[PDB]
Structure formats: structure tokens, C-alpha cells
Amino acid sequence: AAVDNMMVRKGDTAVLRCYLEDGASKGAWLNRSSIIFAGGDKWSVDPRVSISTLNKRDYSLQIQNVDVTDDGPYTCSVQTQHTPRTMQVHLTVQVPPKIYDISNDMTVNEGTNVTLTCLATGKPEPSISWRHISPSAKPFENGQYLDIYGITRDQAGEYECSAENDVSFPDVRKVKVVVNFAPTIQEIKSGTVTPGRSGLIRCEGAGVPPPAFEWYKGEKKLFNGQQGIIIQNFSTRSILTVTNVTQEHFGNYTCVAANKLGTTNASLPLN
Amino acid sequence: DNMMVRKGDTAVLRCYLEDGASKGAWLNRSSIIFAGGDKWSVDPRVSISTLNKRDYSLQIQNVDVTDDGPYTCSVQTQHTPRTMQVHLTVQVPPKIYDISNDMTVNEGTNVTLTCLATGKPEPSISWRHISPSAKPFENGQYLDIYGITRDQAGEYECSAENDVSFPDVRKVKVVVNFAPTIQEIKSGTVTPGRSGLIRCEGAGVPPPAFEWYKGEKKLFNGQQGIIIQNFSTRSILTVTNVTQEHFGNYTCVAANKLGTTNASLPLN
Ligand SMILES: *[C@@H]1O[C@H](CO)[C@@H](O[C@@H]2O[C@H](CO)[C@@H](O[C@@H]3O[C@H](CO)[C@@H](O)[C@H](O)[C@@H]3O)[C@H](O)[C@H]2NC(C)=O)[C@H](O)[C@H]1NC(C)=O
Ligand SMILES: *[C@@H]1O[C@H](CO)[C@@H](O[C@@H]2O[C@H](CO)[C@@H](O[C@@H]3O[C@H](CO)[C@@H](O)[C@H](O)[C@@H]3O)[C@H](O)[C@H]2NC(C)=O)[C@H](O)[C@H]1NC(C)=O
Ligand SMILES: *[C@@H]1O[C@H](CO[C@@H]2O[C@@H](C)[C@@H](O)[C@@H](O)[C@@H]2O)[C@@H](O)[C@H](O)[C@H]1NC(C)=O
Ligand SMILES: *[C@@H]1O[C@H](CO)[C@@H](O)[C@H](O)[C@H]1NC(C)=O
Ligand SMILES: [Ca+2]
Ligand SMILES: [Ca+2]
């Protein structure tokens, strides 16, 4: 009368141990109450099941390509002069986790309500954790679903779903969320200007899609290479250069950043 | 004695008289400007600034580089006249008068940016690449860039300073073209009864044009329920319903004027 446990991943080869009682002593394996082997004779038809015999008294049960259906107690009854000896083995077949459905990469507008979904299998059933890959760690409470109400431009990026069950390495998939928003002028600063020399105005801006920059002065649009000015537009900024800053140039300049979702303005005088 | 007065300012060359009936006289190198209250110069900029009676200072308005040189004030006295020679030095803030215009070049070409400026003293010209990852460049009118890479594009700043007033600063936009590169291609969950997606992120200047091929067969935006969304930096293939007929190796292609490139990915 003995008991033992054994845990094996799905697919592995299990070897349930059993020892015979010297010569003229045979063994027999049971599956709950179904006979698998008795001595050298096989009762099971499962080709995965065999007897692994290394020593003359080794009567271990060898199950190949184990599956979750094999879970349960296996009993080895050993013949003897007196009451047979019973060695019982509880087989538990575990399955690594695997995500089988996750929200696909998306593009949404700022302020909308988003819900990410992640579903995974595994034995034991896995715990599903969400995580936002950003300098702000912000570990999110567990759950298959991550609700994001009023999504901000700062909440964009890759989101990581992690399904763990302590069996093996957890499965990890990602989702790319792009948040579109109307442009925002973060800064507008002009440089010093010697009278006869040139003047510069930076206009830093953000926006998804990237914003198109325009420059104005009193409702009149300024153009590159016309009237003695130079507008150089970059991905995140635009620079207005006034060649010769005479007294007839002072005034309020206005930078404009617009995309598909909206616009924005910012004014500044020329020093 | 020396004095520095940048162009346009009003210069006041100081010369104080001795007590009693002592008159002064100002010279320009060796040309007489004033003698007492009488003016020899015709320059209307030149006058005598007098606070108290002993003040015989010379007031030059709107100074120019032509006024550079020594000025001498001779004041009569009981013995040899007393002199107060002052060397006037007129300085000029720097001014860029020619700078390379915004340009577009291919990757690997040899580029030379130019920036020329005047100023008194002659200004030092500094080139600077406005980029998070960049190394400053030696001063000089010319910035040589051999084998320009896509990472060397962006905003270049010429700054000409001579410590007089504020420095002049102009900029140049350099665009570097290069053949497109597919940085990533990723598919989501493959499951009948759900939507399938394949994103294809790519870079390229000019921006690349995206094409999709299913097992060497081109795909169209409305061919058997599929949807192709082409953006500036990525293309997304959306299979409405993932039937068994859509399984296979999908191929994203990104091409521009300078070249092309592809990247494949299977579904299950
Ligand atoms: C130990 O005993 C258990 C329980 O009797 C055996 O599990 C039985 O295992 C087989 C094969 O793993 C299962 O069969 C299958 O049926 C499903 C449909 O239900 C089919 O999709 C599969 O292809 C396969 O034909 C069977 O359901 C399962 N019985 C129970 C009650 O769960 C196990 O095989 C035994 N181990 C041995 C003999 O080594
Ligand atoms: C002090 O003396 C010097 C010379 O001893 C004077 O420089 C002279 O300055 C005048 C104007 O200030 C110059 O004349 C101009 O010439 C330009 C062309 O160069 C012309 O476009 C103008 O219309 C004007 O005619 C003159 O050339 C220059 N001579 C020299 C030798 O430098 C200076 O003006 C005197 N400053 C005083 C008295 O405050
Ligand atoms: C680009 O320049 C190559 C040589 O650059 C040379 O190396 C630099 C560092 C300087 O020392 C310069 O004086 C040298 O001449 C040429 O071999 C190459 O042909 C040039 N490319 C083109 C398109 O002309
Ligand atoms: C998002 O959720 C808020 C409450 O958190 C609700 O007021 C709003 O109507 C929701 N928006 C959508 C589009 O469901
Ligand atoms: Ca030129
Ligand atoms: Ca050179």
C-alpha cells in the first residue's frame, strides 16, 4: 500500500514506477478499474501504453504522448506470498498556456471607449494579465478584458497580454493601438533679432496623423520664398524665417497645425 | 585709450577742459572737426555734447565703419597742450548673406552645405545638426557631408557670431531619399468567424507604395471580401472572414523611386 504523484506536460512520456516482489512475482497495472497489463500480457488497445522493463523486477508503466484524458489514479498490484502490495500513482497531465484570441491592431480616435480582449487555454486554466508597454509601468488588474474609457493620446502604443499558469513559459501576445487626435502646438518661441538681421520662430506641434503647418500674419497666409521669408516644415515642427526684419515687420504672427481630425492656432510677436 | 561702438549707435568721445579760459579742439586722424564752438566738419552727425562748462566731448551720431580711426582732443594749457587721443573702433553684428537652400538628395551622395556671413570683426560660422543623435561639426563656412545617410537628414543650423549684438542664425532643410525598408509585419489571431489582420510597417523617402500578394497573386482592395488600407508609413490587410481559403503565405511589398522590398508571413 503506497502512493505517489507525477506531473507531466501534454505529449511527454510518463513512466509510472512499480517494483516486483522477487522471483515468481508478477505485477498488473490498472486504470482506475480498467486493466491495462497483467504480467507480460496486455489488456489495453492503446498503442501508447507499454511496460518499460530495465531490471528483471522493473514493472513500470510507460505512457507515450500523454493527454489530459489520462489524468487519474493508476494502481500496480504485485503478487506475493501474502497480501499483494499496492503501489498507486496519481497522474496529472498539464498543458502550457496558449492565447487563441486577442484583439487585432487597431486605430481609434482620441476619447473613444476601447475594450481589448484576450482569451487563452491551458491546464490549469491560466491567469490573463494585461500590461501597457510605456515608461509608466502601470500594472493592470487581471482579467481577459481591458476597458479603456476616454482614451488619450498618451495611452497609445503596444499592449501586452500575458497568460500564465505556472506550468511552463506563459504565452505573450501584443496589440498595437494608434490614437488619432487633433494637433496640439506645444511651444511657439521666437529668437532674438538684430534689426537688419533675420528672425526665427519655432512652432513645435504633435498630431496623429502628423500635422500640416501653415503660417499667417493678420489673416494673410505667408508663403515660402515670397516677400522675403522662408518656411521650413518638418515632421514635428515648422520654422518661419524673416530675412530682413524692418520696422514694417513687427506684429502678431500665427502658426497653424491641422490634420484630418481638427486644427489649432498659436500667436506670437516678432522680437 | 580705446573705445568700441557698434554700427548705428551714438558715440560720445570724452574730453574734459581745464579750469579758466581753456578751449578744446577735436581732430579726425589729422583733420580738424571742432575748435572751440566753431565747426570745421560738414557732417551733421558730428556735434559737441556739453553737460557742464568743462565738458568738450565729441558726439558722433549713427557711427559707421568709415569713422574708424584715431580721434585726438587738444586742450590748450599754460604749457604744451594736453591731448586725449581715442581710437574709435566700430563693430558690426554678423549677417548671413548666402546659405544653401533646402535640398533633396539620395542616400550615399556627397553633400556640401554653404553659409557665408559678414561682420566686424569677421564672424565665426558654426554648423549644427538639430537632431537627438548628432555630433557637432568644426566651424567653417562649408559643411562637407560625404556619404550622407538617411539618419543625417533633417534640420541644419548655421550660426554666425562675433560677440557683437546677437548672432545671426539661419537654417537649411536636408531631405535624404533612400530605398524602402519593411521594419515589421505581424498578424493577429487566425480564427474562422472573426476578422483577420496583417500590418506592414515600412519606411522610405519618398514614402513607399504598398502592394499585397497572396501566394504570388496580387490583391485588390475589394477582391473577395478583403480590404487593403494603405497609409504613409504602413499598410494593413484585413480579411473580413477568415475562411480556410485565405490560409497561406501573404506578401507585403513596398516600393518607391529608388527601389523596392518585400516581406512575407503565413496565416496558421
Ligand atoms: C485511463 O482511463 C481514461 C478514462 O477511461 C482513458 O481516457 C479515455 O482516453 C481516450 C483517449 O485519450 C478518450 O478518447 C477519445 O474520445 C474523444 C471524444 O470524446 C475523441 O475526440 C478522441 O480522439 C478519443 O477517441 C476517452 O474519452 C477517455 N475516456 C474518458 C472517460 O475520459 C485513458 O485513455 C486511460 N489511459 C490508458 C488506458 O493508458
Ligand atoms: C573721419 O575721417 C575719415 C577719413 O579720414 C572719414 O571717412 C570718410 O567718411 C566718409 C563718410 O563718413 C566717406 O564718404 C562716403 O564715401 C562713400 C563711398 O565710400 C559714399 O557712398 C558716400 O556717399 C560718402 O561720399 C569717405 O569715403 C571716408 N574716407 C575715408 C578715407 O575713410 C570719416 O567720415 C570721418 N568721421 C567724422 C569726421 O566723424
Ligand atoms: C565622394 O567623395 C569620395 C572621396 O571623399 C574623399 O574623402 C573625404 C573624406 C575627403 O577627404 C575628400 O577630400 C576625399 O576626396 C569620392 O571617392 C567619391 O567619388 C565622391 N562621390 C561622388 C558621387 O562624387
Ligand atoms: C464611455 O463610457 C462613459 C462612462 O465611463 C460613457 O459616459 C460614454 O457614453 C461611453 N462612450 C461610448 C462611446 O460608449
Ligand atoms: Ca545660393
Ligand atoms: Ca571643404
Image (cartoon, coloured by chain):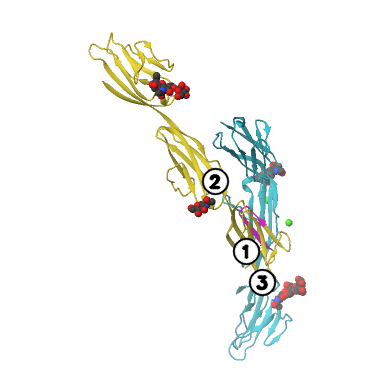
Chain colours: A yellow, B cyan
Percent x, y of residue B89: 65, 71
User: In this orientation, which residue lies closer to the viewer: B75 or A188?
Assistant: A188
Q: Is residue B191 above or below residue B121?
A: above
- Whether the magenta-drawn stretch holds residue B17 is answered as no
- Residue A109 is left or right of residue B27, and the answer is left
Q: Amino acid at mark 3?
A: Lys
Marks 2, 1: nearer the viewer: 2
Q: Write the start and end of the magenta stretch as one range.
A: A232-242
Q: The N terminus of chain A lies in which quarter of the figure?
A: top left
Which residue is disc 3 drawn over? B7
Q: Would you identify the image quadrant in which residue A251 lies?
A: bottom right
Count the marks: 3
Question: Distance of mark 3 from mark 2, alpha carbons?
Answer: 59 Å
Q: Amino acid at mark 1?
A: Pro
Residue A195 spot, x, y in % from top left: 66, 69
**Which residue bears the numbered disc 1?**
B167
Dot 3 crowding, Cα within 10 Å, few <14, some 14–19, many 20+: some
The residue located at (48%, 40%) in the rendering is A161
Residue B258: give x, y in percent of width and height.
70, 41
Q: Which label was assigned to residue B231?
A: none
Return the x and y of residue A152 as percentages of the image width and height: 52, 53
Is residue A57 visible from the viewing direction of this image? no
- Distance CA(mark 2)–CA(mark 1): 45 Å
